[PDB]
Image 1: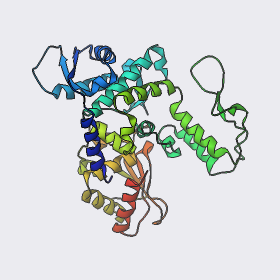
Image 2: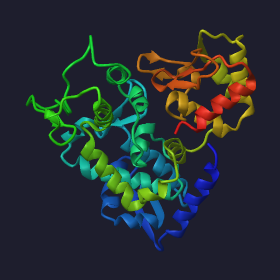
Image 3: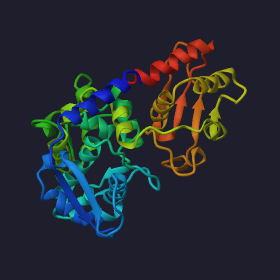
Image 4: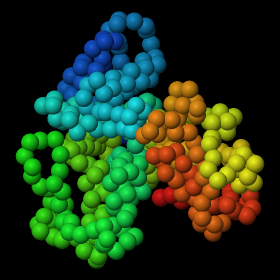
Length: 374
């Protein structure tokens, strides 16, 4: 968003100064890639991954170049991320980035594999290698130890989000009663209970606490069924790249560091945008497009994650954007008044754009929302 270039160079320098001598060799077959990569990497010390890397596919091919590193991180990235291994699964369907599968527990060694994946993604970052990862912004928030907001919820469970929203800005009734600081959970035949805090199953939710309740229910919704997995992943990543080295980045910057910056096709974007209470002839829309045309590609990318929840576009361009209902094109809807700030609903690839009075005001308001979002 701003001094991102500086933060990036700073990270690069940090990795360079921490580089370790000698090297590590990785011998894997083009179709046993996942399993052998796992065995070899886990048999090495985590700091060994900070040494030079020599990946020799014993599909016993070419001669030389970190093009194989790039291919490896690319390939393995799709294998580890492939839901066929039961570690990760897909989000809002038939879409694409991914989520830690609560049922990974089937594999009794899933935690060993999550540690491996964490080491591998930290390794990619340490060597400035890009991966086709599908991690969500909130997962990145977790990596950075940034508290999840109720907005983050909106992009994961619209139903859960709607109930917590009501509980928030609204006093308990005509729809509300007794709720406690516990959750009476999922997957297992027991009919049991989980406390959100010490003795929580006995603490009634009131019109004074409810704010902590909301906080605790949000975090629980994100890590439910995946706490162990998440911890295993972060511990592995941390041994290779200390999470502290990332403290200056926000979740949107972290995503870009892993997938890489890409150019946005403005014509594809414009012809595949839909509108609500706005038209291509609305002055606000004419200004919106003039604004996207004028700014940096980095601003464009931040705007995409603000609205869609990611900087990555599916194969096929904007015409293929998906929601949790199937087709969900980029949408701009008019709301509130010119004094409001723009807002978004990533689950719907929707931007709420107040009817501003001038280009300058639109520009100023969008930029603030795009960068200052937190």
